[PDB]
Amino acid sequence: MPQLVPFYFMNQLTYGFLLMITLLILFSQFFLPMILRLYVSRLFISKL
Amino acid sequence: VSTLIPPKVVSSKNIGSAPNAKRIANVVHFYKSLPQGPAPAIKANTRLARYKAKYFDGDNASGKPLWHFALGIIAFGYSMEYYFH
């Protein structure tokens, strides 16, 4: 199958694993903590 | 005999009850409170702050942006089909 046999396996795969590391960092430092703002904000609202 | 001096001494009723904690919270929160919050998102400008405003605001979540977003990717590969064929 040409979609499972290019010669570009390592080329593709390099760009692929780069996307994973990017997203991991992106979630971890940015996007997960902005939901945690919703959680904490709710608990402060809970206090008031 | 001569009355004791407690009734005329007060100085720890201000930690003595629970709404003191709430009071010191809501003197800060409400005193510097705004009448209304700032924003429900508004940036994406380039004639696309309108795209976000119509579709990705709190006003509605409807299938129109989905269709639009789908169609962009369809337009890419459909043109490329004739680049491949």
Image: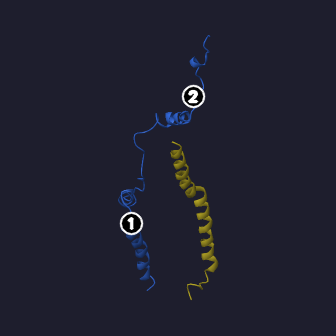
Label the yellow chain with its letter: A
Query: Measured along the vertical axis of the image, is residue B76 above or below residue B24?
Result: below
Dot 2: chain letter: B
Dot 1: chain letter: B
Q: Quick one: quadrant of the N terminus of chain B?
A: top right
Q: Name which residue lies at 53% across and 43% down.
A: A47
In the rendered image, residue A38, in percent from the top left (x then y), is placed at 52, 52
Nearer to the camera, B52 or B32: B32
**Front label number (1 vs 2):** 2
Q: Name which residue lies at 61% across and 60% down.
A: A25
Residue type, numbered disc 1: Pro
Residue type, numbered disc 2: Asn
In this view, the residue farthest toward the front is: B1
Q: Sequence order check: which comes first, mark 1 or mark 2?
A: 2
Give the image quarter of residue A26: bottom right
- Measure the alpha-carbon separation of dots 1 and 2: 55 Å
In the rendered image, residue B15, in percent from the top left (x then y), is placed at 59, 30
Q: Which mark is residue B14?
A: 2
Colour used to depict chain B in the structure image: blue
What is the crowding at mark 2: few (fewer than 14 residues within 10 Å), some, or many (at least 20)? few
Q: Which mark is residue B65?
A: 1
Q: Name which residue lies at 58% across and 64% down.
A: A23
